[PDB]
Amino acid sequence: EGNSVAGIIKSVNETSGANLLSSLKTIKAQAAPIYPAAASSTGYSTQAK
Amino acid sequence: AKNASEVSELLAKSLAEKAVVTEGGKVVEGFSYVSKAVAAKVIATRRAEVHE
Image 1 (cartoon, helix red, strand yellow):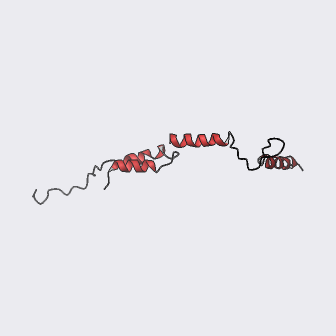
Image 2 (image 1 turned 60 degrees about the horizontal axis):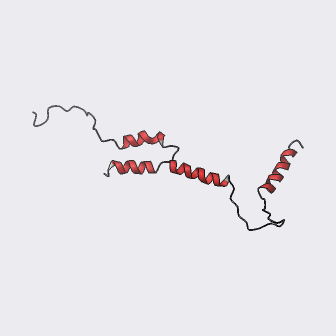
């Protein structure tokens, strides 16, 4: 996993001037940190029991 | 017949865009000039790709 600034720098450099502002929220969300989703419950683990 | 006015203009423009430069009555063949609309597109595509 390379860092997201070099992903921002690359994915802005390989973008034409016509589709630039259309594609910024793609690059904004592709370089977001992962905040993992609230999964299914599976309550009361082995050590919790 | 009713498009013959358009036949004449393309005869003129093909001779107009293939125009030769005369200095003293005689032509200077092998003379290359760059227009002020050609050079204004070289400025405009360079002002576009630096603004990008």
